[PDB]
Amino acid sequence: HRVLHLRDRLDLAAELKLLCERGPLVRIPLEDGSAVHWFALGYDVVREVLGSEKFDKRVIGMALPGNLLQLDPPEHTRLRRMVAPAFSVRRMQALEPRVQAIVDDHLDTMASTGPPVEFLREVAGPMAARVACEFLGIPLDDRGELIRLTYMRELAARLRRDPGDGMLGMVARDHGADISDEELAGLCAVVMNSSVEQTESCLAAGTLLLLEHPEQFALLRERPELGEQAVEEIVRYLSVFEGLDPRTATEDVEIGGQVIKKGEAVFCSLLAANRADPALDGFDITRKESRHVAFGHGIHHCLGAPLARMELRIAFTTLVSRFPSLRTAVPAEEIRFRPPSSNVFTLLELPLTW
Ligand code: HEM
């Protein structure tokens, strides 16, 4: 369903805009009669689908342990409840100064190398990866290699036998016998993946978005208290996680005024839900409350959202303050974005100068 990923730079492609005009829930019977699929395109219907207990995440026509996105209740609940305490408000507050210092480290490297910089590979990527290591509690001597590769079972088993700090230590200390080596390794892999894919892309493309709106780049500098609002507006506008794994109805269920039959698959487009409403779509960090589903909704709602929200706030606020003269080293119109795919949305490189 490639149409759900068609963009014009950061905005929706006309072809996808045209599709959204067909209403927030669109029935898509396959041309071969093999199935009936649905596109959930509106904010309310996407929330209705994702909150419903009447859908599962069955495979339809690689499964890895510790991957919450491939579990349904009650197994999903069992694993999620064991890892959830790593993201409490208490734990992000304890972690904030150390994340601030990691961000400052990478912006120190940037200011010393001097311009230009390829911001994606040289700043955003490493920053996101290093924050992930700190959150996870990766031992210092493993971080360089772990990041270079993005082994995991060997790493997870060793840390499990001697709990450290961070999320992995907490999990092994409090649930050592209830989580296997492969499941702990799977958690580690998802966190690294979500950091070097989703978070890195938000950092790089969000910097571009701010640079394309220099009034707001500067506003965040003069009013850093806007950081939290800025993050919500950035993740809404970017929608780097564009479309979700299908939800299959386990029984007939009425959604958005239509009957989704047992066995039919619903594809939620976060991109469309976040962007298709022309009314209030303009990028504006002074919006006090953003209407978006950039982190999903329901039992699979992004487990890392507290970390992502804190890391992005720290990164963007510090960046605009330390580099008021930042600008793209090429015209914004020349930036390459990855072509339509179910993979995370990202630009391919971001040359910056200052
Ligand atoms: C800007 C960055 C991020 C965005 C936009 C994002 C987005 C999302 C979305 C939309 C989902 C729901 C997928 C679905 O329901 O099919 C999700 C799930 C998840 N995310 Fe994030 N994510 C981000 C960063 C992170 C980070 C930093 C972590 C670190 C732990 C993380 C861990 C997870 C996990 C484990 C799940 C699965 C939860 C479950 O199935 O119960 N993500 N993410």
Image (cartoon, rainbow, N blue to C red):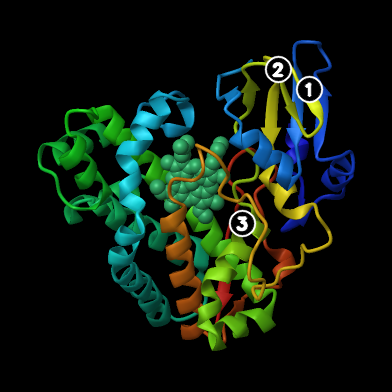
Q: Quadrant of residue 324 in the image? A: bottom right
Q: Residues within 10 Å of mark 3 (few under 14, many from 20)?
A: some
Q: Earlier in the sequence, mark 2 or mark 3?
A: 2
Instruction: Residue under label 1, please give it.
Output: 259
The residue at 75%/54% (across/down) is 275
Above or below: residue 202 compared with residue 7: below
In the image, 232 versus 146, the foreground residue is: 232
Q: Determine crowd level at label 2: few under 14, some 14-19, many 20+ residues with C-alpha closer than 10 A.
A: some
Report the residue marked by disc 2: 252
Tag 2's secondary structure? loop
Q: How far is the residue under mark 3 from the one under mark 1?
A: 38 Å
Q: Earlier in the sequence, mark 3 or mark 1?
A: 1
Q: Could you say where residue 84 lies in the image, as x and y percent from the top left?
A: 35, 44
Whether residue 291 is visible to the viewer of this picture, yes or no, is: yes
Q: Residue, x 48% and y 32% (percent of image)?
A: 69
Amino acid marked by disc 3: Leu
User: Alpha carbon of mark 2 to alpha carbon of mark 3: how far?
Assistant: 40 Å
Q: SS at mark 1?
A: strand
Disc 3 secondary structure class: loop
Give the number of marks.
Answer: 3
Q: Amino acid at mark 2?
A: Asp
Residue linked to disc 3 = 347
Q: Nearer the viewer, mark 2 or mark 3?
A: 2
Q: Is residue 10 left or right of residue 158?
A: right
Cβ at disc 2 under 8 Å from ligand 1: no
Closer to the chain start, of discs 1 and 2, is: 2
